[PDB]
Length: 7
Ligand SMILES: *[C@@H]1O[C@H](CO)[C@@H](O)[C@H](O)[C@H]1O[C@@H]1O[C@@H](C)[C@H](O)[C@@H](O)[C@H]1O
Ligand SMILES: *[C@H]1O[C@H](CO)[C@@H](O)[C@H](O)[C@@H]1O
Ligand SMILES: *[C@H]1C[C@H](N)[C@@H](OC)[C@H](C)O1
Ligand SMILES: [Cl-]
Image 1 (cartoon, protein in one colour):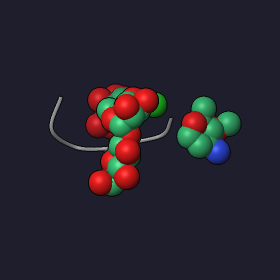
Image 2 (cartoon, rainbow, N blue to C red):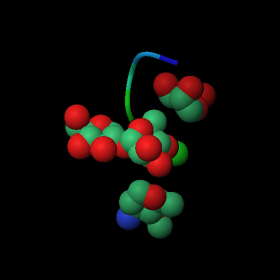
Image 3 (cartoon, protein in one colour):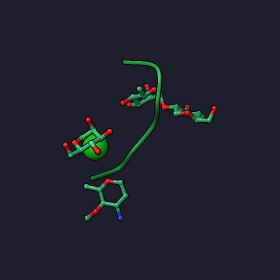
Image 4 (cartoon, helix red, strand yellow):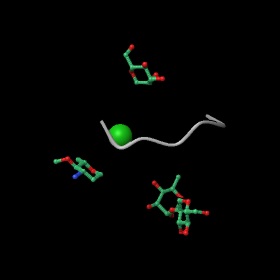
C-alpha cells in the first residue's frame, strides 16, 4: 500500500 483510504 502506501496511501491510506478508507474506501
Ligand atoms: C493508518 O494510518 C494512521 C495514520 O498514521 C494510523 O494512526 C493508523 O493506526 C493506521 O492504521 C493501521 O494501518 C492500516 C493500513 C490498517 O488497515 C489498520 O488496521 C491499522 O493497522
Ligand atoms: C482504492 O481504490 C481506489 C479506486 O481505484 C484508488 O483511488 C485508491 O487509491 C485505492 O487504490
Ligand atoms: C474507513 C472509514 C470509512 N468511514 C469507512 O467507510 C464506510 C471505511 C470502510 O473505512
Ligand atoms: Cl479502504
